[PDB]
Length: 50
Length: 79
Length: 50
Length: 72
Image (cartoon, rainbow over all chains, first blue to last red):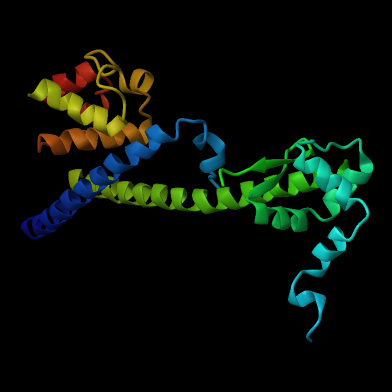
């Protein structure tokens, strides 16, 4: 059973790697907007948590 | 139908140009005078037909402009 | 005086409200996609470690 | 190199200047990276060098000097 579960573990590992790469790529792009919205435009006006 | 003001001009614009205040105002405006809130007659007139006047003067390649403070004036284009 | 000010106000308000509606919506869309993928990555990470 | 690949990752994951990121520059107070920003920073550090880090030992890292110390 532990061997059988380790195969599930490895599937999860590959999935996790893919998701990791995608998340990092998103952050890289979003950084530019953050540097650009330092004008005090973000604090409340743009970031409407509602 | 034919021979009808609407064929050539909007009714409100013709109504404005036919007013007794127009020649004075026109003359002045062309000369560069600014119009504020104190000269009621003129100011009110301007307010009533703003868009028609703007459209009119546009023919000349000049903008009839309204500053935030409520005063009107003429700004010519390069052409 | 009234006739002036009322106008001015109308234009101000309309531009403000529509522009914020137009921009904030997509800004939050992006933020939410990034949040979602990060959350999925963290759940995968924790489950993999355990 | 590792000691400048760390800067490559940190600057482009927090958007701060290369000059700002010194060895002792802490992420939260100097670089301003908050909870999720630091999470993404550690994820990027993992990806760059294709390694993995424990949860507690990773969260212990809260500075450029500490970042390199665990990296190198």
